[PDB]
Image (tube, rainbow, N blue to C red):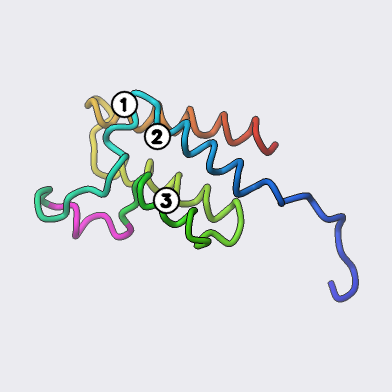
Amino acid sequence: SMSVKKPKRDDSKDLALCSMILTEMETHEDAWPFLLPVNLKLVPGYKKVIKKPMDFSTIREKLSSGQYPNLETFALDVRLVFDNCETFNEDDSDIGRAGHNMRKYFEKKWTDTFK
């Protein structure tokens, strides 16, 4: 409350650490469905169904240009990429499996880097 603060958690490295995580996601072999925005002209249904499209390149640009206020807003966009993927793709598809693999990969790096 006013003039009553919890001890200040050091957030000075968060930008660099989220960048490193994102590099590792970018270079994973199963990243390929996620590297670029889904082409809304060429993928029937995507535009209407997926209200907030997100992809690694778009997160990378947001990150590089100070559009994440804190590390939680960064994790929300990463999770959105996987949530969108589950919304649109069957679990038993290459892309569906890719999404589950990447989300697992991300959540471990997240916990190990910050928790």
> Which residue range is magenta in the image?
45-52
Q: Nearer the viewer, residue 23 or 37?
A: 23
Q: Which residue is mark 2?
A: 26
Q: Earlier in the sequence, mark 1 or mark 3?
A: 3
- Residue 20 lies in the magenta-colored region: no
Front tag of 1 and 3: 3
Q: Is residue 49 magenta?
A: yes
Checking the image for residue 97, the label placed there is 1
Question: Could you tell me which residue is drawn at 90 percent across and 68 percent down?
Answer: 4
How dense is the environment of label 3, judged by Cα within 10 Å: few (below 14), some, or many (20 and up)?
Answer: many
- Looking at this view, is 48 or 37 the one in front? 37
Report helix, strand or loop for mark 2: helix
The three-letter amino acid code for the residue at tag 2 is Glu
* Comes first in the chain, label 2 or label 3: 2
On the rendered structure, is 16 left or right of 97?
Answer: right
Q: Residue at x 61, y 41 (%)?
A: 17
Nearer mark to the viewer, of 2 and 1 = 2
Q: x, y percentage for residue 13? A: 68, 46
Discs 2, 3 touching: Cβ within 8 Å: no
